[PDB]
Amino acid sequence: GQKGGQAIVVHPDYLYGAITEDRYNEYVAKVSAREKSAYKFFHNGMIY
Amino acid sequence: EQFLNAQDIDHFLSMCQNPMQKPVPFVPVLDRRFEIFFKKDSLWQSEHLEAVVDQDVQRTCILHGPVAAQ
Image 1 (tube, rainbow over the protein chains, first blue to last red):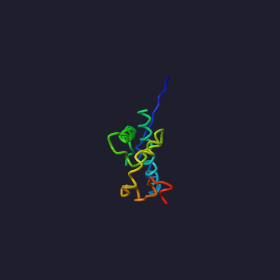
Image 2: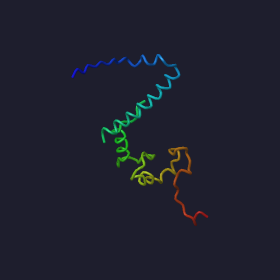
Image 3: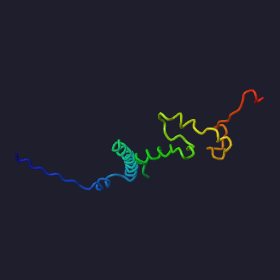
Image 4: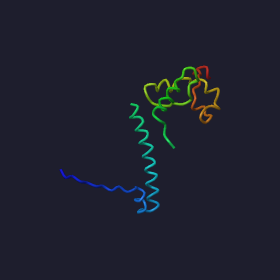
C-alpha cells in the first residue's frame, strides 16, 4: 500500500553530553538501583 | 553488587532446614514456620554468651523457679 518508513537510532551515550556531571551521576546511581531490583523481579518471575 | 538469585534464596532457606546440623542462630524469613524458627534451640545461649549478638543475657532464655529464686 505504498507504506515506506525510515527511523534513525543514535547511540545513547550522545545524550549524556548534554547534561552536567552531577545530573549524570545521580542518574547512574538511580539506574544501578533500578537494575538490581529488575534482576530480582525477573528471576523470581521466571522461576515462579 | 548483585542480589541473590531467587534460586539461591530458595537454596539458602532449604539449607537452613538441614536436620543434621545445628540450628542457624538467626531468623531467615517470616512465614508459616516463624514459630519454629523463633523457638527452636533456645536453651544453650545462656551458657555460651560469646556466641550471642552482643554477649547480652537479656537476649537469652534462662530457666528458673519463682519460689526457689528467693
